[PDB]
Each structure stands twice: as structure tokens, then as C-alpha cells.
Image 1: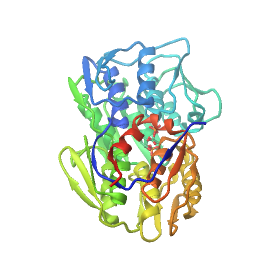
Image 2: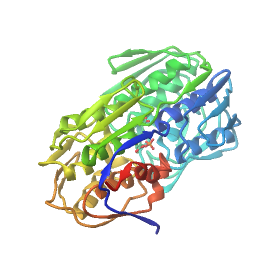
Image 3: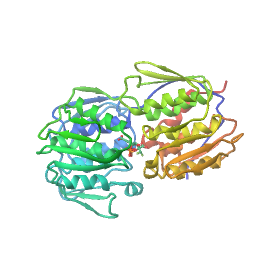
Image 4: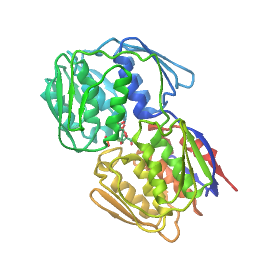
Length: 427
Ligand SMILES: O=C(O)C1=C[C@@H](OP(=O)(O)O)[C@@H](O)[C@H](O[C@@](OP(=O)(O)O)(C(=O)O)C(F)F)C1
């Protein structure tokens, strides 16, 4: 078991050029593969989730080339649905943005493909998506536990009236939205009730528009899609920097700055996690907005009590930043933390208590009362990139912290610790 020990960081200050957005990167790659023409993506993220998507596209027959640093990709569009037979297995690692979107897209036409991944992926739900795809005509088989990967897809999604549950993940609706335009018949997608992580649907619709497709969004309760469409290459496309990855560095400044500026995202970004900056401002930090940067300067840090459903991933960063705030912080309406890279409510509460906090682990919320002073802990990371990045902030105090399995950050940010060190100052 590898580990990394972070010594106390006296102050943070500096500029970080953000790695590419994982959410945008995987959507752009799949749309480029389905599109007609050559797409040149720049500022593409090089991480495990993107590598698994690229490997899947290679296995499906898509041609592309990558630059030396793997941030520039020239993709040759397939000009329509991707195809493979013989129960070809695509191993998708831990990537939800490959698993959910491909589970839907590969249901177009006739195929015989199996989707699987790491053990944890076999524990992340996909039943709501499968239910919707079947209503549209798809033939899908669960090879292990019902409602979870791995899946054998045999095609048949033609469109029609499809209902989808949006209460657990926005990725199921995202997958349907990307797939429906290419189906032969028109599709009306009806949301059964609530829709969580709503800002990610805006990311999906933005990418679809870039690739030539628009749909009718009726107040996020129903989406009307015309079938028989085709995606078209936009030529060159610049991938936004990752706003979720930015959260760690902006929070670092709110706690121990200094001023930290992140470039690659700004006030015009399509990512919902830029709203993380507004939470730091509510806590007492100073935020500066630019067209291609967001910066945070240390002010003060006061506890908050907020519904975080609109920024579930960046909300985890507030949970460790809360260790440094005045008062008790409560983060609400975050049930799906339980079904991601690990059960994050269980994990976050467990590890926060290890450094001294008093924590109430609610079914769908977490309440955190910081200790007078933090203590040392060897932090378990649950094969979850965000547990490692969130707990790295413990070192912005008088105590060191040891992070187990630091390489798990590679899901979205292989160079995380090098970047945190770049802004760490001794004076
Ligand atoms: O559509 C997207 O791009 C995502 C939407 C969210 O999921 P929900 O709609 O289910 O709330 C994020 O939490 C998810 O990021 C994570 O990763 P995956 O891409 O799903 O593997 C993450 O980086 O931590 C997370 F869900 F674990 C990526």
C-alpha cells in the first residue's frame, strides 16, 4: 500500500493552469467519434477516465492520434452509430462518463457488446438507464447483479416515448439525450420526478449543440428529440479546464492564502462547479472573476448550511475546508454521494473524525463541527480520487497528514500533488 505524507503548508499563493475537464472531455470524444468529419480537441484531459474512453473507441474501430502530452487529439468521425459484434468486451475502468453514455449509444442499431469495468463500477447503479433504453426498444442483459454493470447490449433502441428516473444520477438522462438524435424515430424523454445534478445536463446540451444538435427542453421535465439527425465536427474545439479539479486550489487559498488563480475556466464556463467559488465567497473568502480565470484570496472562513445538490463533487471540498471554518457546517441534499467512487457520506464522515472533527453522518447530508486543533491521521481513500484530493487540505494546518494510495487521483488528475506543491510556500 503506497502512501504520501504532506508536511504542513505555511501559505499558498500562485497560478495553476487547469488540466482539462473530464466531463467535457469524455462527452466531446464520444460525440466526435459519432460525428461526420475530423474533430481536433485541444486541452483534452489525460487521465484514467479519458484513457478508458479512448481505448473503447479504438476497440470499436475509431481512428485518432494524440499529441506527446495527450492533450491534443485528432479524431476521425465514424459518420454515425458505432458498431461491434461477437460480444466484444469494453473495459471502462471507473469512468461513469464512458459507462453510462456508451450503454445508451451502443444500443443504436444491431450490436453485440459487453460493457464492464473495475469492481467498484459493478457497484454503481445503471438500472434507471437500462429501464429507459428498454422502453425505447433496446435489448439489454445484466450479466451479474440486476441493475448494475456488466451489461450485454444487443441493440434495438429506435426511439419513442421513454420515461427515465432522474433521482439517482443525471448521467442516465445525459446518455439518453446524446443517443436519441441518431435513433430512427422521434423520442420524448419524460423525467419521472426529481432530477439531481441538474447542471451536468446543461453541459451535455452545450456539447450536443457544438456538434450540431438541439432538442426541446421543457423545464427539465420533458425533452422532445427529433430522430434521424447526424452529429457534425465543429473543426477545432477547446476543452474547458476542470472546475471540479479547480475546487481544491481555490479552497486552499480560502484557508491559507494568499491568492490562488486557476486558469482555463471563467465566468462563461458551462460547468456547474464554478459555483463552488460562490460558496467560498459565502464563507468569507474574496473571489475575482475573469474570462479565463477565477481567483480566490484569503478573507475569513465561516461555517454554512446549504443544499449542495447543484455541486455534488465540489461540495466534498467544502467538507474538508469546514475543518478550518468558524462554526458547524451542514451540507444537504447529497444522497448520491453514496453511489459514486465509494459511499462518500460514510467515507467522508469516517476520515473527518480521524483528524478530530465531530461529525453527524445523515442519510443525505453531513454535519461537521471542527476540533480546536487537528491531529495526525493516515487517511484511507477508498479508491476515490476525491477523497485523496479533499484530504490533502488537512496539511494547510500545523499537522502533517498521510494519504494512502495517492495515485488514485489519476481518475481525473494524475498530477494533482505536483500542482498543489507548486502553490505551496514556506513563507
Ligand atoms: O455527467 C457528468 O459528467 C458527471 C455528473 C456527476 O454524477 P451524478 O449525475 O450521478 O451526480 C459527477 O458526480 C460525475 O463525476 C464523478 O465521476 P463519474 O464520471 O460518474 O465516474 C466524479 O468525478 O467523482 C462521480 F460521479 F463519481 C460526472
